[PDB]
Image: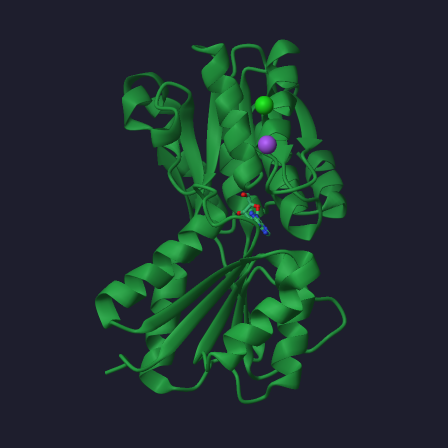
Amino acid sequence: KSEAKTVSLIVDGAFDDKGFNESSSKAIRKLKADLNINIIEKASTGNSYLGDIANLEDGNSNLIWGIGFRLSDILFQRASENVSVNYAIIEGVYDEIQIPKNLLNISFRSEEVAFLAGYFASKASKTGKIGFVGGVRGKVLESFMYGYEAGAKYANSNIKVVSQYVGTFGDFGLGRSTASNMYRDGVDIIFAAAGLSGIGVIEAAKELGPDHYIIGVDQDQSYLAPNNVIVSAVKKVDSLMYSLTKKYLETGVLDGGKTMFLGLKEDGLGLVLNENLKSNYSEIYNKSLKIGQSIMNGIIKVPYDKVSYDNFVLQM
Ligand SMILES: Nc1ncnc2c1ncn2[C@@H]1O[C@H](CO)[C@@H](O)[C@H]1O
Ligand SMILES: [Cl-]
Ligand code: NA
């Protein structure tokens, strides 16, 4: 078996985000539980990526996972320079370069699940004004923002959407103040797509009580605020990391040198309802799932950047 092997994991910021980074740790710990492999987990930061990952290498890791686009260039450099080490990255963002054979990149079509979140929030909102709180801007987050705004307009052409960015995935207090300002300005539902920062958005909703709703992200976040999180736009990082790593442990060769793309139809993303609010939002949830099937069948082409969004809006 694979018991002698080691799989390592490096994230940016804290593991304990109730979402994206946490899901990567869940996968690695489940691999340890099921296969009895060795694991190493490291929470890192930009000023020390190079040293932290060089250390996972020196621990003779058989596979090193990096999580999130902020690790893109470092994971690429280390893979390029260490041909005998295998690396995989969740959401590497690369422009010019060709991916080396010992690096596997995973890309999620986040705009697809964000479209479901926007459609849902737009149908559910009583004020007709909804919010989006993002983490760090860039290609990944813009896919969430434009997918959300497009799905919202698809549900109601005159929907009002307020978008703000915390600017980091690790500022809970700024998530809270951003959300508090939105709720005070007539927003009644906020999609928090902001890592740990978004948990502060949830805190703001809890502090304001009933009628301040959240669309959660990455994992089912209804348990964080069972009266306020209506639905969650999940990203199935843990399932994918487990299955890809298990295959790698069986073959010993990384299926790398490429980017694997996952959206709704690959079961890489999904929309998960809070059962405590079922009687009240089930009809909208079911309509949202039909929208998801239209996306999966290629009927709705979901925008993901400014150009595709502006075209989508003009062609509605
Ligand atoms: N530490 C992080 N680093 C990079 N991207 C992140 C991080 N946390 C969250 N994200 C991204 O923001 C989205 C919403 O939390 C996630 O699905 C992921 O794409
Ligand atoms: Cl605070
Ligand atoms: Na804080």
